[PDB]
Length: 408
Image 1 (cartoon, helix red, strand yellow):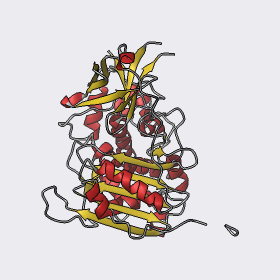
Image 2 (tube, helix red, strand yellow; image 1 turned 45 degrees about the vertical axis):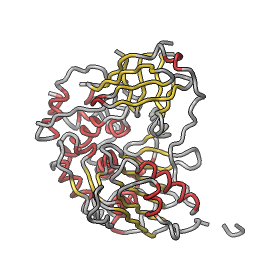
Image 3 (cartoon, rainbow, N blue to C red; image 1 turned 180 degrees about the vertical axis):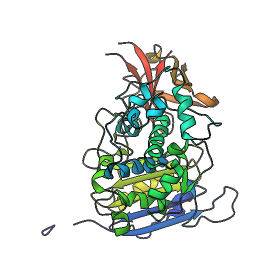
Image 4 (tube, rainbow, N blue to C red; image 1 turned 30 degrees about the vertical axis):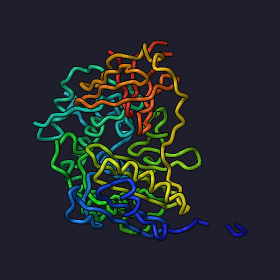
């Protein structure tokens, strides 16, 4: 008070085993770098039917949090002067040009504002080069507009291909040699599509995830991390890209990291929660706090919320996206919104089933949503918001899970 402080230290006596049992998470890790000190928690088993208990070194899929590594490796080459964030990647991939996708800058690709579809799957492509060649041969089809946020794995595949062109290594070699090994981690590459690797192919521990987050701190607390990446280059990832409104996902988005929290407490980070496992990363460079949670269960979303609420009681206020949904509305207000919406070859069909909206997702999946005012809906249970988009006045697109899907 009179002479100033930084706040309280790491949470004392936080029983992550109890919280994990309350949320019925099979196993996972939480790791926290706070005021120069690393604290880790492990709970449960690596497998659902029991077996080996999770230890500090257990590996969990990072899912989309892999993107933070890919972008960090891009910005690392930025400080070295080997690439330019605002130049069209066609100048860095002149062989691929021989296109709307190559007119995008690395800033746009890492920010999901490059106007690209969410997915392009090619399991037979042996390289990011052959993967890109096949994607550029597709018809342009239904793509979101450049400059607006629409989550895209394709953008991160292109960004990974730029890394290969600049360094002369494969993406897996570059990320290991330039990032994974110098960070001092045992992070492994999962055996998946080469074209999906830059978007979601890394796996490792929560402690090792924190090591990446420490790199983005104003003081990383380690000379090995300090010399690894240019602080001026990484700060670009700490700044929002203008015009990127990631409705339903985050309050903002920069070149490789989401922004989470209200004004005055915006945190950097990234989540990954496909495939029945969860990964959550949050970074606050100013306060010097990094938190990462890994779990092998979809209930890790509930555990993350309980960890955030528990950390708040310990004077650590993690930034999270908690938007104010519009008031509930009768489902009939969405009569003009029913139809099919497409992003690349992905399609979502919207219908009205009694009082709720029903979303038919690709892959046979299905989700119900609560109808709200202003063309907005809330996923039943999780509360994740989506919305239908009108041309300033008919509806022509759907914003769902951070992706723009144009109405057929």
